[PDB]
Image (cartoon, rainbow, N blue to C red):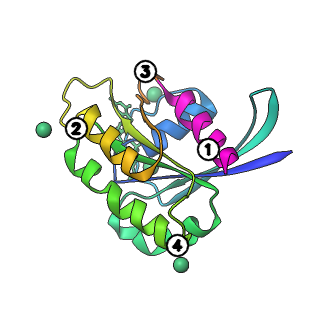
């Protein structure tokens, strides 16, 4: 079937793993074990089409920036994640976006901007700021909570679909 190779990128602790785990395995990971590189594979139905999701969960910890170029070459689309209660995580998105941009040598890489932890009342990144950033990229912005499951399906399936529009 059609296999979609998604990569989840973003700063440490923003919820990349929890998002992926909630999606593929339908539960919330409450603890924080930093990731190096984990791979997930799951067959799903999106717009009547049975497709395979191949999802690479990546390190947001700087102890692993060197591995970035490899995963950015392979992937067909990137879930670019920050957390809405962490302004520095939002400021970190540019580096990921530019890096992806250089690697693929394209201004038109399938990507989705995700502001995670929208359950948390302690917001410092306004939706408006992220809408403006994503607009400059020509991609969607979608808020999520790995904790409540809010928007998690919309995020990943929107990404799958973005890999289609191209
Ligand atoms: N309240 C809340 N907590 C969240 C959410 N997503 C992740 N967390 C919490 O934030 C912490 C970090 O989550 P994790 O998924 O491990 O982050 P990560 O981006 O994968 N980290 P790393 O880059 O180091 O691998 C965990 O304690 C997790 O429960 C969310 O939507 N809401
Ligand atoms: Ca749990
Ligand atoms: Ca390159
Ligand atoms: Mg992780
Ligand atoms: Mg402000």
- In the image, residue 122 sits, relative to residue 130, either above or below, namely above
Comes first in the chain, label 2 or label 3: 2
Look at the numbered disc 4 and say if its residue's Cβ is closer than 8 Å to ligand 3.
yes
Residue at the farthest right position: 1
Q: Which residue corresponds to the image point at 54% horizontal and 73% vertical from the top-left?
A: 105
Comes first in the chain, label 4 or label 2: 4
Name the one closer to the observer, 153 or 158.
158
- In the image, residue 67 sits, relative to residue 153, either above or below, namely below
- In the image, residue 34 sits, relative to residue 132, either above or below, namely below
Task: Determine the secondary structure under disc 1.
Answer: helix
User: What is the span of residues highlighted in magenta in the rendered image?
Assistant: 151-166
User: Picture coordinates of residue 6 (x, y %)?
Assistant: 61, 50
Comes first in the chain, label 1 or label 4: 4
**What residue is disc 2 on?**
125
Mark nearer the viewer, 4 or 3: 4
Q: In which quarter of the image is residue 83?
A: top left
Comes first in the chain, label 3 or label 1: 3
Q: Could you give the CA–CA distance between mark 2 and mark 3, rounded to whole angstroms?
A: 19 Å
User: Picture coordinates of residue 101 (x, y %)?
Assistant: 47, 66
Dot 2, crowdedness within 10 Å: few (<14), some or many (≥20)? some
Is residue 164 located in the magenta-colored stretch of the structure?
Answer: yes
Look at the numbered disc 3 and say if its residue's Cβ is closer than 8 Å to ligand 1.
yes
């Amino acid at each position: 079937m059609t296999e979609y190779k998604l990569v989840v990128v973003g700063a440490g602790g923003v919820g990349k793993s929890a998002l992926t785990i909630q999606l593929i395995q339908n539960h919330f990971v409450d603890e924080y074990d930093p990731t190096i590189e984990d791979s997930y594979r799951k067959q799903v139905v999106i717009d009547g089409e049975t497709c395979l999701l191949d999802i690479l969960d990546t390190a947001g910890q700087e102890e692993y920036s060197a591995m970035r170029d490899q995963y950015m070459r392979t992937g067909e689309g990137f879930l670019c994640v920050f957390a809405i209660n962490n302004t520095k995580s939002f400021e970190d998105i540019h580096q990921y976006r530019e890096q992806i941009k250089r690697v693929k040598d394209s201004d038109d890489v399938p990507m989705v901007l995700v502001g995670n932890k929208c359950d948390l009342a302690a917001r410092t990144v306004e939706s408006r700021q992220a809408q403006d950033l994503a607009r400059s990229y020509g991609i969607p912005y979608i808020e999520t909570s790995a904790k409540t499951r809010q928007g998690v399906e919309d995020a990943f399936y929107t990404l799958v679909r973005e890999i289609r529009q191209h």
